[PDB]
């Protein structure tokens, strides 16, 4: 239940404006002042109000209090409003901070969701390694078999060709050292070739 | 050739800290095996016969070598490893599903709470009880300090 | 023509090797043995005149699930 903004519009701190408007349509701007002065002159004159030291006192006190409000009123007013607005700002900051705290909690939980969703890369990496290792082993086996068969084939053809080489060189050296042991016909041919000098 | 393309930082995010070494070894294994597969072609070049038919004068050695090679069926190894990791994946999916449902519950609850705080009464109209219900941290501990002002004097 | 009589006669004598397994070599075996020895024990050590046999190894593996 909110507070109504303003007060009651009292005058002199002693009379509310309701009384003045109350008398307005009947005697207006001259009503209250005249009633007041008439009444005070009455209470003076007819020994209604005694004048004694108490007048001295109460006048001093009214003076102190009027000076007091008229001077230190605005300060206490604005101090009150300081307290109010400050408490209000602090409450607003508590509210915003709590909202932001829970919002951060929500976003972090959403991040958790995203990651644990991402989880499955683990299993597909395992799968990848499995299949890759398997096919690697298989291809290694095939190259092993092709390598060993090629090796036997080469070995045989190589020893074959090497024997070919050795026998061929032995044969040519045999024929050279054999033709040697074997007629002036060659000499007559020599004279013929020299006759072919020209 | 059935391979699953992968991120790798996404992998790195999902390794609980107890087994970072195993996972790192798995990554290294992945890359070394990829290189090894690239390090050799798919199938061997099958040996021709003519080059040896007309050169290897050995009797039936080239022939029966070629034939027993034809009569050779290299054992293609079967895994027996994938089905179990699939089952493990299954269980992990189940656990993740239940965890994520619980998290969505907590999420909608946080949402409702935030909305309550969002629908606040204008503070100037708020009785101390409504401030209390809006924040239990604004509640005097009337239990531990039962006399006025129910809180540390110096705290005032 | 000396070397031409040489070529013809020596070629006809060399093709006459049906009777001579190394055509009157009578030596060079001392090195031929070790030569084919080297060639073998360089290409391998097994019986390289029989068909190759094959063992096939299989990979190592591990515990993969969360421990």
Image (cartoon, coloured by chain):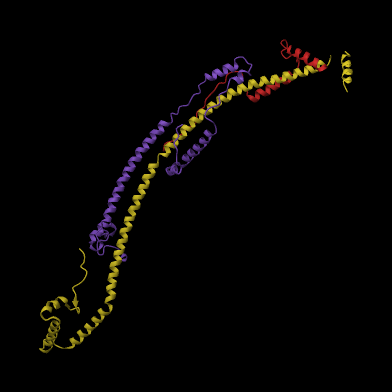
Chain colours: A yellow, B purple, C red
Q: Position of residue B109 (x, y in %)?
A: 28, 49
Residue B18, quarter of the rendered image? top left
| Figure check: A69 above or below B44 | below
Q: Residue at the spot x=61%, y=20% of the render?
A: B52
Residue B17 x/y as whole percent: 44, 44
> Which quadrant: the N terminus of chain A?
bottom left
Closer to the camera in the image, C34 or B42: B42
Above or below for A25 versus A44: above
Residue A57 picture location, percent across and down: 20, 85
Furthest residue in direction top, as rendered: C19
The residue at the point 40 percent across, 33 percent down is: B86
- Residue B23 x, y percent position in the rendering: 46, 40
Left or right: B20 with respect to A44? right
From this viewpoint, which residue is outermost toward the front? A198
Foreground pick, C52 / A52? C52
The quadrant the C terminus of chain A occupies is top right
């Amino acid at each position: 239940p909110p507070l109504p903004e303003y007060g009651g519009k009292v005058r002199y701190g002693l009379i509310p404006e309701e009384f003045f408007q109350f008398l307005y349509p009947k005697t207006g701007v001259t009503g209250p002042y005249v009633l007041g002065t008439g009444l005070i002159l009455y209470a003076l004159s007819k020994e209604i109000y005694v004048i004694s030291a108490e007048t001295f006192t109460a006048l001093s006190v009214l003076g102190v209090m009027v000076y007091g409000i008229k001077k230190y009123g605005p300060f206490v007013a604005d101090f009150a409003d300081k307290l109010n607005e400050q408490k209000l700002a602090q409450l607003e900051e508590a509210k915003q901070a709590s909202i932001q705290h829970i919002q951060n909690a929500i976003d972090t939980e959403k991040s958790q969701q995203a990651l644990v969703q991402k989880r499955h890369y683990l299993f597909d990496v395992q799968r990848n390694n499995i299949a890759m290792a398997l096919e690697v082993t298989y291809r290694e086996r095939l190259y092993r078999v092709y390598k060993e068969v090629k090796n036997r084939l080469d070995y045989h053809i190589s020893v074959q060709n090497m024997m070919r080489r050795k026998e061929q060189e032995h044969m040519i050296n045999w024929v050279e050292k054999h033709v040697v042991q074997s007629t002036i016909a060659k000499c007559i041919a020599d004279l013929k070739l020299l006759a072919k000098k020209a | 050739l059935a391979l699953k393309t992968i991120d790798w930082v996404a992998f790195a995010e999902i390794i609980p800290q107890n087994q970072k070494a195993i996972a790192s070894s798995l990554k290294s294994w992945n890359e070394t095996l990829t290189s090894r597969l690239a390090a050799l072609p798919e199938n061997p070049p099958a040996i021709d016969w003519a080059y040896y038919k007309a050169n290897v004068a050995k009797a039936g050695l080239v022939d029966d070598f070629e034939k027993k090679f034809n009569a050779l069926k290299v054992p293609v190894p079967e895994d027996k490893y994938t089905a179990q990791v699939d089952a493990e994946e299954k269980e992990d999916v189940k656990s993740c599903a239940e965890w994520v449902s619980l998290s969505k519950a907590r999420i909608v609850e946080y949402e409702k709470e935030m909305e309550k705080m969002k629908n606040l009464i204008p503070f100037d109209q708020m009785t101390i009880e409504d401030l209390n219900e809006a924040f239990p941290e604004t509640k005097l501990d009337k239990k531990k300090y039962p006399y006025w002002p129910h809180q540390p004097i110096e705290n005032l | 023509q000396k070397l031409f009589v040489d070529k013809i006669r020596e070629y006809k004598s060399k093709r006459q090797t049906s009777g001579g397994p190394v055509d009157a070599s009578s030596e060079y075996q001392q090195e031929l043995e070790r030569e084919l020895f080297k060639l073998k024990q360089m290409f391998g050590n097994a019986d390289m005149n029989t068909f190759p046999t094959f063992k096939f190894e299989d990979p190592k593996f591990e515990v993969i699930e969360k421990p």
